[PDB]
Image (cartoon, rainbow, N blue to C red; front, side):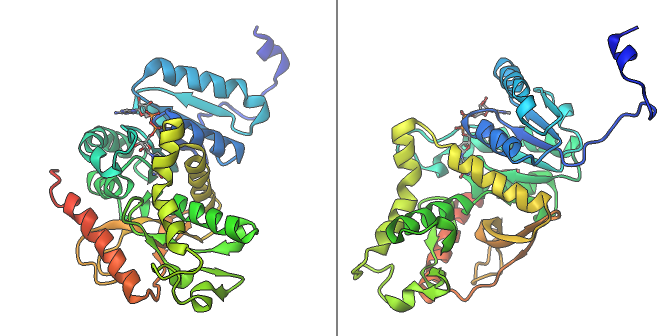
Length: 332
Ligand SMILES: NC(=O)c1ccc[n+]([C@@H]2O[C@H](COP(=O)([O-])OP(=O)(O)OC[C@H]3O[C@@H](n4cnc5c(N)ncnc54)[C@H](O)[C@@H]3O)[C@@H](O)[C@H]2O)c1
């Protein structure tokens, strides 16, 4: 007999078991692995599944995480090119595909990554028909639209990581200038996770003190403090980090784990993530971009109607138009 047989006396009959809060990460690159480590570090899942086309890399990553199992609270970690390993996921994070080279627009990746997604998305829904999908691959807003169309899932189950990262960066820069913790500075970057994102100056506050009320020129070119530059630093951050280290991953890995925590803990916390915004702020096409949304175990259940300033509406409209310009020309 096995020493297993000698040591372990069953009390319950053998049974094949179904994970409670399984997460799949598709793509084990810089971003995929950073999401994986953040998810594991927060004990957010009882079963982590990884998928990539690079079989050796994939196995290598799986084994490295497994070797750290002692320090974790995730009893099953599996990896394969074959989507069968992904069955019964609560949440599937897609980080797979091409990324920006230095100075390259996220929008320039669309054609290559649409082809990647045309293969990936149907496999995901095949093995996890009841899942939530979080799209991370760029351009994140467009690929969220693409995923929604390809998957046939309702709007509340298809979410782009969107501006959760931009707002994090914004709140960090704000906190830098004020000497407080980013969590105590409040402000929203909305619209495209990209060059046309929108700083919602009207909602920026510390302890409910409206900063645009203290400084009505906030966000203009007529600004004593220089807030427009903060937004510009938010816009430029990815390019700057890509120029320095080649890609970004840590902040996004943390942003993604933040979103997953809200969903799997059923918290209904509000995050700026990418959703279908048709009919809001006079946006008349099926555009996906970020607005503040309520996230819980069902996914993205609500959007917050804001009282945006006229200029902010115009900026958000421009973002929708930029994104629609690309969306409209897509096939299948
Ligand atoms: N949304 C955000 O805020 C944000 C932030 C950073 C990066 N990104 C995007 O995340 C994506 C990943 O970036 P990265 O640095 O991890 O790239 P990377 O090259 O390190 O990793 C990409 C991984 O995707 C895998 N892959 C390619 N085609 C695949 C397919 N058909 N099926 C399964 N896997 C496939 C590749 O083999 C590779 O391992 C890029 O699109 C990048 O622009 C988004």
